[PDB]
Length: 51
Length: 262
Length: 51
Ligand SMILES: [Zn+2]
Image 1 (cartoon, each protein chain N blue to C red):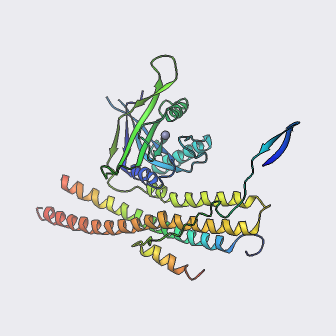
Image 2 (image 1 turned 90 degrees about the vertical axis):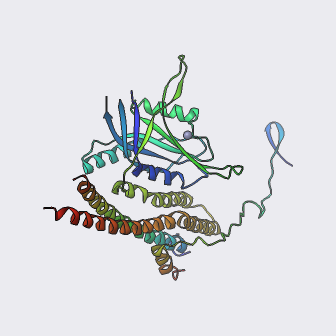
Image 3 (image 1 turned 180 degrees about the horizontal axis):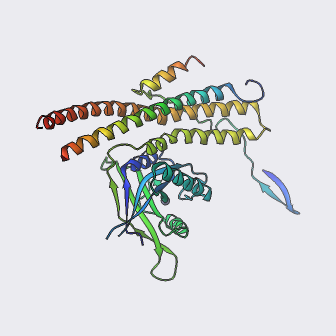
């Protein structure tokens, strides 16, 4: 436990331990977001090579 | 004073597509129109302006006088462009997974807007309603105003008759308003990211993490919004081409039927 | 990470989004024109039916 002075008396203070569990929140979207859009496909495909 | 509201489906589509954009939060916008008389006072709503909500949280939907200035500017612009006497006449917001009726906060906000002008009316869209028992979906809408309670307490709700006017085709104003959704979402992400980058006293690995988050967020925006919107516009262009061909055929048929009689 | 802050992914993705936005703007303009043509033709057909 943590202690700190306040009114001359010492009161407890909350303590937390940082860990990987704190909102890593793995996503990875599966199932294709397929669109019958010619323009969308053309644009994504043109700018795919970029990265 | 006001007796009824007519809404052009042209703008109803923008309102509904804005309501179906997200279920996780409530969204809002403004309604532009005119005053009309019969016998009966009616409000004709022609177009709407989509807004980005800053306060967020549940049930806390309010409009800044800044957005009211923007809406009056849009009203003047549309009145001069169309030559119609268009003023900002109302507001709308979405209630996903929530009853279509207005909350006490919705009614108090409607009263706060009526203090500006008694001609102001409110709209509500009830979105994604789930019911695995019936396996049926629902989407609802309502219009309302506020009035002082039966005794000298505080404002209470009152219902306004609302009808939808068939606007056979989509107006340029409403297309230019509907294509604002992806732009406004991208601007929201960009402003959040700029507020993140404002804290110069920051780790580099944290900046890489935030960059990854930003990339995935805009990828989600494109996968869920821009892509389907563009696909719908392509499909509508195909529908319009087919409809134009059929109507041209019908015009030629009627021209041939009527022209030879003289 | 590039020079003077910024990130390469940020600008790549922003430019990709701007390209898709311009595609949507162009398609919006042309679909609006198609809607105007439909309005004209429909008014003609309905007036001829009235006659
Ligand atoms: Zn509400």
